[PDB]
Image 1 (cartoon, rainbow, N blue to C red):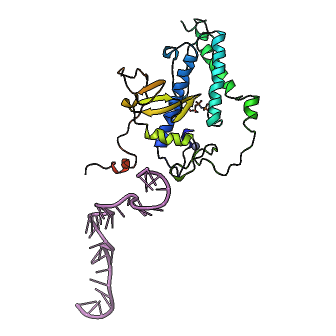
Image 2 (image 1 turned 180 degrees about the horizontal axis):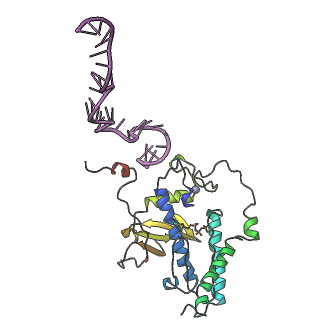
Length: 250
RNA sequence: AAUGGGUAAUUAUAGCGAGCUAGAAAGCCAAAG
Ligand SMILES: Nc1ncnc2c1ncn2[C@@H]1O[C@H](COP(=O)(O)OP(=O)(O)NP(=O)(O)O)[C@@H](O)[C@H]1O
Ligand SMILES: [Zn+2]
């Protein structure tokens, strides 16, 4: 999805910066919104990274059914507007107080129990109804999104035929430089079930109406009382100057 | 003494054996959007 960019693409690297940043907010938000379908918060998440995020949850039935139902919810969201290019696969290993110095073959042997369930669910993706609804036919499409070859919701953003996600990514590339990224319900790129992402300035938080706010690269607590993400980014200049600034002063 | 004749050595020696500048640019594309 990220290196779907090719030769003769409208976006140079803003369509690549804003695309590898967007999936990282999606990986952040799956981790966040999974923890309030449960009763938990950010402490229980051991790590979040490039789509991978390890947790510590409770070995009980009301959590496992919440895991399965939220997994089906987010995969319905990914099928609604990414069409089997993105698939999130949960997986959970039950363990006692065995991550404590049967000392060698107890810790990693249950950390790998979740990776086996992921590899089993990554390999047998869907079920009956959600694949019969896939290849149901019924579409007289003439055109397609020339970035990702999708069909639904075609617009003419800068006289090229692009889709709903790949116009939201240009809008997010105009909004990428901000520190604050809020989740609304109907604005910008969708990142979940009834949950969309929008980049916002600081003093526009009273104008906008959100539910959860992320602040990027900040250790001060701030005013919005946000969730602190940390994405590495830097821009000294635009890309086309990087050859011309390759000279010395002489 | 005349008379017959020439015979030996060197066949090039000492050097420099290339130096410096340029080492791909400008367009299409990409950017500008
Ligand atoms: N948002 C992102 N932007 C840029 N690079 C990323 C991002 N997320 C992950 N990556 C990179 O992608 C790597 C993982 O690639 P990938 O093969 O997709 O792993 P995966 O999540 O297991 N997908 P798959 O290989 O199909 O199972 C990471 O190690 C990162 O280097
Ligand atoms: Zn697209």
